[PDB]
Amino acid sequence: ASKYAVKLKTDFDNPRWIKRHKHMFDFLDINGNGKITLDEIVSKASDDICAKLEATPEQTKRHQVCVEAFFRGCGMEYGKEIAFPQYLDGWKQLATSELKKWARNEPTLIREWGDAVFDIFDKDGSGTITLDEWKAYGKISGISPSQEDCEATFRHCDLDNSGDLDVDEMTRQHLGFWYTLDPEADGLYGNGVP
Ligand SMILES: O=C(Cc1ccc(O)cc1)Nc1ncc(-c2ccc(O)cc2)nc1Cc1ccccc1
Ligand SMILES: [Ca+2]
Ligand SMILES: [Ca+2]
Ligand SMILES: [Ca+2]
């Protein structure tokens, strides 16, 4: 099954990797000082997104704890200001480590994060995401506020064409965008992220 088939390794010191994370870095650098902190990342990637999605307090805590683990895996910490090259070093370590974990059947940070987001999207608790529950990632995060190709990204996430999404599909498309830079996932976050 495509949703469980992931590359064993990736390449990192290329223009697509660098530009993708640069656009995210600049967006998450709330105070614009050229350094990113875990405070800034959690504010944008967890506080604002869970508020927009009307997550419950338990869902929001869970989500935040997953975001913190994930970015601690990149070398982030509260109050620690990190410049873009060291941020990139961290993401290289994280992606390398996580792809090895996947191939060895060890739990990954990205899959746990997927679980937390999936639970929030699955408003009726059905165990799948239907098109009416789906959202444009670029729009809910604010980095591409004009993104409206929800149905196209939904269809591409739906690897088995069941007409709905499971958590493994959502996680596979997310990992495709951020670890392995799969061309099929390009555009997932709208025009604000190359
Ligand atoms: O995209 C999401 C939500 C999500 C969806 C599916 C899934 O399986 C897991 C998570 N979160 C996300 N996932 C990844 C990253 C992320 C990636 C790269 C990077 O350098 C920084 C943050 N950020 C974010 C939040 C965010 C903040 C700001 C603008 C857009 C999105
Ligand atoms: Ca900053
Ligand atoms: Ca549902
Ligand atoms: Ca499906």
Image: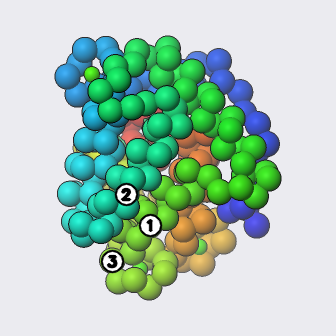
Amino acid type at mark 1: Phe
Q: Position of residue 178 (x, y in %)?
A: 55, 40
Q: Position of residue 115 (x, y in %)?
A: 49, 64
Q: Residues within 10 Å of mark 3 (few under 14, many from 20)?
A: some
Answer yes or no: disc 3 within 8 Å of ligand 3.
yes
Q: Which mark is residue 123?
A: 3
Which residue is found at the position 45% from the left and 74% from the top? 129
Q: CA distance from mark 3 to mark 2?
A: 15 Å
Q: Quadrant of residue 94?
A: top right
Which residue is found at the position 76% from the left and 67% from the top? 1
Q: Secondary structure at mark 3?
A: loop
Q: Residues within 10 Å of mark 1 (few under 14, many from 20)?
A: many
Amino acid type at mark 3: Lys
Q: Position of residue 177 (x, y in %)?
A: 56, 43
Q: Is residue 6 visible?
A: no
Q: Is residue 113 visible?
A: yes
Taking 1 as reference, is 185 left or right?
A: left
Ligand 1 - quadrant of the structure image: top left
Residue that badge 1 annotates: 118
Residue depth check, mark 3 versus mark 2: number of the one nearer the observer: 2
Residue that badge 2 annotates: 63
Amino acid type at mark 2: His
Residue depth check, mark 1 versus mark 2: number of the one nearer the observer: 2
* In this view, 165 is above or below 153: below
Q: Position of residue 12 (x, y in %)?
A: 66, 24
Which residue is found at the position 43% from the left and 30% from the top? 76
* In this view, 81 is above or below 62: above
Front position in the image: 61 or 5: 61
Between disc 1 and disc 2, whose residue precedes? 2
